[PDB]
Every structure is written in C-alpha cells, then in structure tokens.
Length: 548
Ligand SMILES: OC[C@H]1O[C@@H](O)[C@H](O)[C@@H](O)[C@@H]1O
Ligand SMILES: OC[C@H]1O[C@H](O)[C@H](O)[C@@H](O)[C@@H]1O
Ligand SMILES: OC[C@H]1O[C@H](O)[C@H](O)[C@@H](O)[C@@H]1O
Ligand code: NA
Picture (spheres, rainbow, N blue to C red):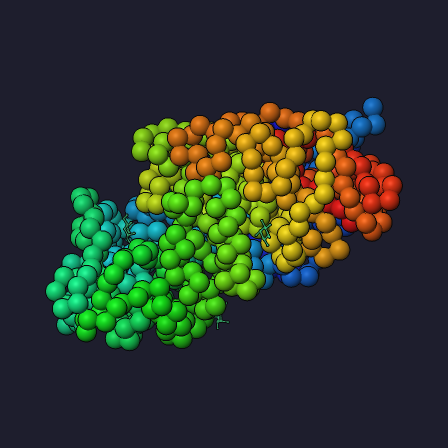
C-alpha cells in the first residue's frame, strides 16, 4: 500500500476512439507519465496536474498500463499506476461484479457504489434479486410499472433505484444484466398462464412438482419448469420483453439450481435438464436478439451442453469437490475445451465462506492468492459489488475488506486489465525449463505443492510468459480459504533464475501486482546458448516474466 498516488480514470473501459480522462489525487515534481503496451513505452509526457486526457490507440481489445515516475540523486520511483482496457464490447475480457441492494438508496450513494466498481474496471454488473418474481420479473405492466415492489425476501425494491443504477453503470461503460432463474415459479403465479404441462416433477405420474425449499424469510418455495418446454419458453420470452421495455438492461443473467437428480416431464419422460438449457438459450436470444445472455453452469452442470450456444462468455459457480487450486484451473481448462477456445470464463467462487457465517474481515492473503491463480490462468472472478461476496446469497455482507485488501485488490484488477492480452487472448500453456540460480526459490510446475513456487508458462505470439505463483508458505491448497487461515507469503527478493530458451532473447521484462503497482520493469539478462539468466526483484504472491 506504498503507492504515493492514487491514479484513476473516468470510465471502467473505453471503446476505440474514446478519450481517457485521468485523476491523480496529488502531484509531484520532476515526474513523467509513461503509457505502456505489453511492457513497451508508446507515449511519455510530463506529469503536469491532477487531471489530463489521453486518446489511446484505436486497435480493439487492447490493455495498457499507465505508470507515473519521479526522478529523485538521479534515481526514479514509481508513484502510481492504472490499467486501461480498450474493448468495443465486454465479452472478450469480462470483469463481472454485482449489485444486491435496490431499496431507497440516494443517487449519491448509488454513485459511490458504481464509482468504486469502476476503479476496479468492472465492465458489467449482475443485478441480483432486483426482480419481483422468478415467473414475472417485472412488477406491474409495461404501461403501468410498479414504482415499488417486494422481492423474494419481501424487502422493498425501488424502480427508480434499478433504473438509476442501470443509468449509472451505463455512464461508466458497464453492461447491466438482470438476474433471474431459467425456470423459476413462486407460489403466487397464475396457473392459467403456467400450465401443469410445463413443470418438472420428482415422479413420473406428474404427482409432486420438483421444488427448491426456502425457509423464512423467503416468501415461497421455488417450483421448477422445463427449459425446453416451448409454452414455457414463449411465456418467459414475454416476461423478458416486458422487463426490457421498462428497464434498460443489456441482457439476462440466467441462473439455475444445478443438478436436480432424476426429475420428469408432465408426460413422465426424463427432464434431463442439462440437455434442455441449449434450447432455452437459443429461444431466449431469438426473442431478444439485441440482448446479452450469460448462464451459470452450477458446479459445471450444463456447461458442456451450453458451451457452443449464444452466450457472451462462460460462467461457473464453483462448489465441492472442486475445492483445490488445481480444481479452479481445471474449470478454466475445461471451459476452454468445451467452448473450443471461443469464450473466456467468470468464476463465482465465494471466499472465506464458512467465516462469512458471522460478521468479520476477509482474510486478505486468501483473497489475493486465489485471484493470483485465477488471473494468471486467464480467468476472471465475480466478487465485487457494494461489498465482496462471502456467500451465494449476494446481499450477505457479513465480511468486510480491510483498507489494505481494497488497495491490493485494486492493483490486481489493474494488473489483469493491463495485461489481458497476455493472460486470456490466445496462446498455449507450456511447462518452462526454469531453475533457481541461488537457492532462494524452491521451484516446481503446476499444479502447486505447499512449500514451492509454481511456474506456469504460456506461449502468446512470439512471447514466452512465465508466471511464478508462491505456495512457499501455503498451509492449504484449498482456494476458498473457508476459515480465513491462509498465510501471507514472505517476500523473496532478487531471486536469480536460469531459463532454457532457444531463440535469441531481445528483452525480458517483469511485472507483478505486488511490486510497483504492476508497472513493467525491464531486467538485465545474459544468454549463453539456450541458457538465459536474470534476477526477479520481488515475489510475494504472483510475478510475471515476459521473454521477447
Ligand atoms: O488452462 C491451463 C492448462 O491448460 C492445459 O492446456 C495445459 O496442459 C495445462 O498444463 C494448463 O494448466
Ligand atoms: O438463496 C436464495 C436464492 O434462491 C434462488 O437462488 C433464487 O432464484 C434467488 O432469488 C434467491 O436469492
Ligand atoms: O457468442 C454469443 C453470440 O452468439 C451469436 O453469435 C448471437 O447471434 C449473438 O447475439 C451472441 O452475442
Ligand atoms: Na471490456
């Protein structure tokens, strides 16, 4: 939290040709703003005030880091950094957050929420439990929408807040996705509209409807309909249209309850929900072709089946037995394969889960290690809204983030924005041949081993990337850090590395969210044959080495 300046930009992301407006919280003398692309300086200018603008290069889907340097005795110091995403649309590089509270909140309170998210470069937002009813997400009618409604826990939801947040998210270049289930009905539905033939039953004689039981303070259990059923699809498409004509959501965050076991259609056939979802997705899209769709594969239920459908990117809510770091990276690897490398993924992976049964703090090194793995592997984490997620019920805010975690996490979002081209824009994973030169690092491959630094290589274009992920001081390899026990890694400094690399090396550079706000630092190096050596300045959680 050493950064002398907080450097922010006005929007979350920028379409090609949009102007970037910067704010620094304070100014220093004899300082230079450097604009970098993949470690290359593309622009330098004098740091001349707190507010200034930059027209970035117009090529689409491009991250940059901006770093301010002071000259002191002729040495320099990084003062502050900010990542910048130039994307036309969010789906290539999704940075998904949420919103959870839609009561009478002031415009300036909403602004502070959206602004904070913006500083993490959040590029769209899942609006969780904004809706009236699973089976009728719009309260009232299109011509007469209800200004205030009660949600599934009977709390008050204001139209003006929903509309307002949509407008605020829009002013910051963010997309707004409305939450609903694919197939939810609560007990006040109209039976003349959702007929008996549309439900899923736990037995074969259309006796007992399948249902997710919710106790107090929820108003109803959730009945389940068949996503493939055409009357259902047409019914809900009308509901979505209704919503879209009232609230200017960009699309529908489709949620579900995961594997229901053996369930039946009315007619006694097997409902086989994972093979019903593809049809549902296509029906939703064809009824609203200008609106976005993302669907949650709960613990990967449906994922193979849906990966080639009309989804912006893939999403996976992670549960047991997927609890290891190596299980997180397996979900990312699987989602690549299922989508034949067409779609990146967002992970809903609730940290400090057990601890969040009570008020407390998030365990900073757990949150950072987990995001260092996810972001190093080209994933993305839905974790931030008005607060950070501790539970699948998004409004729960039992755990707070320290000011240290806030700070750090801002630099991690900066890092994964700035270096998105290296992290999740094509290439192939490789196992680098790398060894400590000095004994300072105890080096292994991935998947990780407690006590060792795991090296992960990726060939992106003509670049070789090596990510160092520090498990030296890890006391579990469980991502969730459910009880907040994980350790803070000891710093390792000036660690000599040896790397086999045929092909002349032109430049090696380093960047770490744990060192100089992720600014790129060029390293010295020698090359004898295939043997290259160099020193990394710092490893805490996650360093990235780039060989060109
Ligand atoms: O998704 C990253 C994973 O991708 C696979 O292609 C590689 O073989 C693994 O080594 C790697 O961890
Ligand atoms: O856990 C309670 C949750 O159950 C379901 O996921 C509902 O769709 C959602 O509205 C509610 O928040
Ligand atoms: O991959 C998702 C995309 O699938 C198709 O190309 C749809 O027509 C488009 O609306 C959607 O965004
Ligand atoms: Na974007």
